[PDB]
Image 1 (cartoon, rainbow, N blue to C red):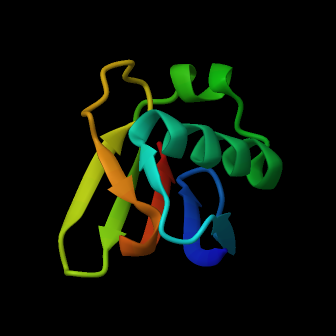
Image 2 (cartoon, rainbow, N blue to C red; image 1 turned 120 degrees about the horizontal axis):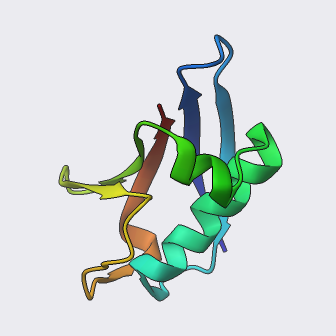
Length: 98
């Protein structure tokens, strides 16, 4: 549907990941949904597993919206905001591990 650019930065690596996540256009998704997509590329691109996220000092991602607002999420947390956000409002995502 739509392509959302993202980066993955890890304190244990000089070279950062720069790629695109695919979403269905104009679809409402939860932060739990977004977590699944973020965790998948973390494991595929950097070999960072759920175990590694738990063992990290800090694991988070920032969703930047087209209107200039943003939301920072702690990847270790199991508490999510009913947050239903629309896929088409996402501008970019920055993922950061320790």
